[PDB]
Amino acid sequence: KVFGRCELAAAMKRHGLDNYRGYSLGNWVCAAKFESNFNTQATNRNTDGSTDYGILQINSRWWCNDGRTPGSRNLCNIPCSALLSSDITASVNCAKKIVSDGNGMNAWVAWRNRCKGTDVQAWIRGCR
Ligand SMILES: [Cl-]
Ligand SMILES: [Cl-]
Ligand SMILES: [Cl-]
Image (tube, rainbow, N blue to C red; front, side, top):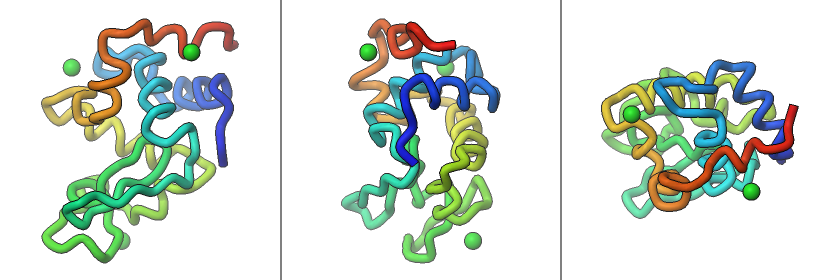
């Protein structure tokens, strides 16, 4: 599913991301825009052999099991395919574990490089 901007904003707010660990809703929507272009089906391979999955591009090295990342952990205890569902619950639940692990949203390279320090509330401007 390719979400609309305001459609994703509303889904992320319903699942508890608005000001989760201090990060307003626009931070998460900006993050999803540049990680996946709002596409729950997005995948991208990493040079180390891991793969990033879903609207927030969660890495199989640490967070999900895809059966092909040697020496990996599965800290969200889920298959990486669950992060590809048109239902974003698994992705959001796992994102909360990531953003709580010490580095905040700096865990997402795209957030640090394209959202951090910008006017992220523009990503939610004009939505209900
Ligand atoms: Cl599994
Ligand atoms: Cl933080
Ligand atoms: Cl914008």
